Image (cartoon, rainbow, N blue to C red):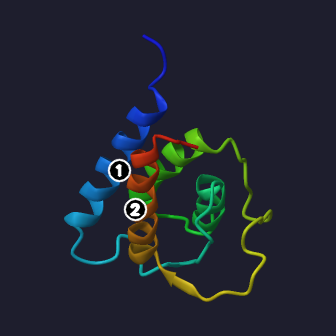
């Protein structure tokens, strides 16, 4: 069987992300907040580096693997690409929700990253 197609991976990613945030009573991480990013064609690469700032949260380790599948960006806790602007940090729960609108959005155009 060949790898999972791109559109199929997005649906798998959207369904899994929704499942862990819909049944969440409180922030999955210890209230960890992440830097806001501009949602653009490089959402997976930009979103990944912002998450590299969250450690100890197993609930998102799988998310990190799936996001990498869309962005071969090996980012280290020392290398940063989108955190150039001095924006404010936001709760991870809100970060996923804001990203969720864009995830299903590319599905309508079928243009995956």
Name above or below for residue 17 compared with residue 71: below
* In the displayed structure image, the side of residue 8 where residue 48 appears, left or right: right
Compare residues 71 and 52 and report the one nearer the observer: 71
* In the displayed structure image, the side of residue 66 where residue 70 appears, left or right: right
Name above or below for residue 107 compared with residue 58: above
- Residue under circle 2? 100
**Label at residue 77:** none
**Farthest front residue in view:** 109
- Where residue 52 appears, as percent x and y from the top left, is 62, 62
Compare residues 78 and 69 and report the one nearer the observer: 69
Name above or below for residue 36 compared with residue 7: below
CA gap between label 1 and label 2 equals 7 Å
- Where residue 14 appears, as percent x and y from the top left, is 35, 50
- Residue under circle 1? 14
Q: CB under 8 Å between callouts 1 and 2? A: yes
Q: Which residue is painted at 73% across and 87% down in the image?
A: 86
Where, by quadrant of the figure, is residue 1 drawn? top left
Compare residues 81 and 55 and report the one nearer the observer: 81
Q: Which residue is painted at 58% across and 43% down in the image?
A: 113
- Where residue 36 appears, as percent x and y from the top left, is 59, 77
Q: Report helix, strand or loop for mark 1.
A: helix
């Amino acid at each position: 069987m060949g790898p999972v197609p791109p559109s199929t991976a997005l649906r798998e990613l959207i369904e899994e992300l929704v499942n862990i945030t819909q049944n969440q009573k409180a922030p999955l991480c210890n209230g960890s907040m992440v830097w806001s990013i501009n949602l653009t064609a490089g959402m997976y690469c930009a979103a990944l580096e912002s998450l590299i700032n969250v450690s100890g949260c197993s609930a998102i380790e799988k998310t990190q693997r799936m996001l990498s599948g869309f962005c071969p960006h090996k980012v280290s806790a020392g290398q940063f690409s989108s955190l150039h602007v001095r924006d404010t940090k936001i709760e991870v729960a809100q970060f996923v929700k804001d990203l969720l609108l864009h995830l299903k959005k590319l599905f309508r155009e079928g243009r995956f990253n």
